[PDB]
Image: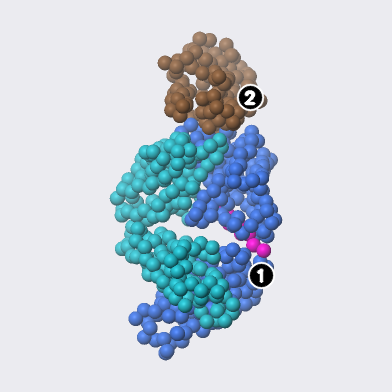
Amino acid sequence: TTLFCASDAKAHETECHNVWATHACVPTDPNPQEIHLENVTENFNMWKNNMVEQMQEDVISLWDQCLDPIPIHYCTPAGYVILKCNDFNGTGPCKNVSSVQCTHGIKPNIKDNWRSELYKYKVVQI
Amino acid sequence: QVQLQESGPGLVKPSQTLSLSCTVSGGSGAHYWSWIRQYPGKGLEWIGYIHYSGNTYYNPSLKSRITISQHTSENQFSLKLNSVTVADTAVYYCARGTRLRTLRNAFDIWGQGTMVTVSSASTKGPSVFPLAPGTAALGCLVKDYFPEPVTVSWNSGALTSGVHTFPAVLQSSGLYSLSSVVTVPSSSLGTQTYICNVNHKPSNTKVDKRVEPK
Amino acid sequence: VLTQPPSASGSPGQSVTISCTGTSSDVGGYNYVSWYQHHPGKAPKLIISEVNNRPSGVPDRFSGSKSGNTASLTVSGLQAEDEAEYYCSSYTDIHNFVFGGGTKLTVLGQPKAAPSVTLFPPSSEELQANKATLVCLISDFYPGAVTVAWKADSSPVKAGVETTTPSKQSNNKYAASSYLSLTPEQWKSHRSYSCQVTHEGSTVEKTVAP
């Protein structure tokens, strides 16, 4: 699905992609949800992940109107949710999953610089 | 499923303080909850919005006249506009703004709109003036009444074809005004007599005006 | 604040395009141009987002664009059901937005007609009763989208003016009405009063005198 970004970017400020984020992202929630999965185990694959399809395109529009980096989060809408692995390299099963609304705060093929941190995350549809 | 319904009081006195509620109905993210008004034509003005987080963002041209708030309780939100003048007469829409990529800074879901009218005016009845003339065209000007509606008909219902009654128009005073007009064979102008039948329930008024040449 | 044309017409099958001129801080300062389809008394549909993006369930035939500070929206292969009013918005500055005045996209189903302008001067009754109103009757035209302006002698007027938005007649053609209310001083000082109505690049202008 199509995601959104959030950041704690300050509305008034000129560092190039603080500028982008203020006009691209919502303010960040200081209390996200991270719920322990009981009992169950889920299959991950960093290499088949359509979160590294959308991030990569926002870095395009970042530069497009560009002319200190801050943390950006990526998050899901209703009907969907992010499962995160608490175990793991990038592929195969994972017993300790928890569900999250957003990713961690990310300092910025740079797709795969993102996969260096993405690997733990995956989307599912309710 | 996600719909929006606006609710509110339709008239307000100048210098008072308008306030409207929009009721979400689907339906629950990172959207924005917005108020946008239509000056019909003109005419489209973003008032402000409030974020799911509680961040408000208003239009700078409203120098402190304005607040927006949330009731996560009844899946609804609301606007307060202060010190209104006749200027603020408009259609008021509520809407969902998104910051999803591919829809950033856009308004995916809208409300059906609802009309809001600013006027001092207590009930007034109309002043009915004629509009004098093969084809000729003649009419009644129905001026300075309140509130709506008004009923016009020509020659006690008999004359129907070629007739057209206009939408009313709110003057800066606070009072309404409209026109009705029919085209006729000028063959019959000193022969066939013509009368418009104005009818204003609010003031329990009924005017039958003669319309004739020169 | 953004500038659109008032009307835009085409027959079934034809292709049409709508300009939306902004400035460098509105359009051409951001790729957050959006477009809304709005049928009357009914809730607006977003149809183009972020300059050229069709949301789900929006047919391949609608399309966005912008060259400089002039964004633009296209409908390729008209159908009867596409007749509506179209607006554009753009993000601007730290959290703010602007719109266009709107454009009536008329899908042609009948022969065009230019407006019949009838301009009634104030009646005797109204004069003798302190008041004066000038009535511009605009009738028998198609497409149903017009634009009025007034003149005292040879000079523009906007205070004391109000105007209807086009309504169908018994015979499926359109009609509208503009008013100029003013005191008898104003009426009988000025040499002439001119109502002028724009329909499709043409501009008809009636005039009356005391």
Residue type beneath disc 1? Thr
Q: Measuring from the top left, give residue C162's x and y in whole percent.
A: 52, 64
The hue of chain B in the figure is blue
In the rendered structure, the answer to whether residue C90 lies left or right of residue B125 reads left
Between C160 and A94, the one lying in front of the other is C160
Between C8 and B5, the one lying in front of the other is C8
Residue depth check, mark 1 versus mark 2: number of the one nearer the observer: 1
**Residue at x 51% of width, y 25% of height:** A16
Between C36 and A42, the one lying in front of the other is C36
Farthest residue in the top direction? A89
Question: Where, quadrant-wise, is the C terminus of chain B in this rendering?
Answer: bottom left
**Residue at x 46% of width, y 35% of height:** C30
Looking at the rendering, the stretch of residues picked out in magenta corresponds to B113-120
User: Element at badge 2?
Assistant: loop
User: Element at badge 1?
Assistant: loop
Q: Which mark is residue B161?
A: none
Q: Residues within 10 Å of mark 1 (few under 14, many from 20)?
A: few
Q: Measuring from the top left, give residue B27's x and y in whole percent.
A: 58, 40
Q: Is residue B116 magenta-colored?
A: yes
Q: Which mark is residue A33?
A: 2
Residue type beneath disc 2? Gln
Between C24 and B180, the one lying in front of the other is C24
**Residue at x 53% of width, y 42% of height:** C97
Which chain is assigned brown?
A
Which chain is assigned cyan?
C
> Can residue C207 be seen at all in this image of the molecule?
yes
**Residue at x 65% of width, y 43% of height:** B68
The residue carrying mark 1 is B123
Q: Chain of mark 1?
A: B
